[PDB]
Image (cartoon, rainbow, N blue to C red; front, side, top):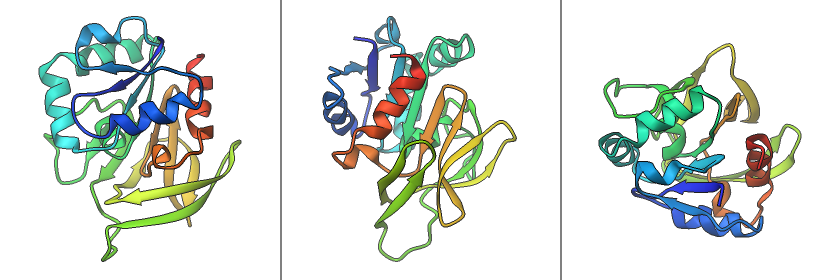
Length: 189
């Protein structure tokens, strides 16, 4: 298996199920050793402060940083995973995270009474994709080398920086595997 889903905490189950539609049997990553042999790693939705704390404690954060830097590992972060990837988390400068993505992300900042909504999104190259948002974080600022692949109105919700992909929505909460395939393709799987 060359595709893994970080399984320290959260909803990795949904991503494994989504990956099955691509004929992939996802490897559950719980130890740094589990990163060996992977071409792609998905960081799931969940509790961002916990995923960050555990990934740091187990040495996974540092190894992932090294792997991405050498270009031997593609990353796809969804919700908590997108927060984990962000270089800056608004209001939580010291929150444990990878921080490779040049972006400023604010946790659960959409400002809607009901903290859950769904929107049809236009994804560059992919087409229309059903976006599922739950206590969704907001991409406040993006670095110059970051590409916006999808927006809700004018707000970026799917961004890419090289082999790092991040979404504020949950593609794994739909039965559409096209965004996952898009990720595997860029990871060279």
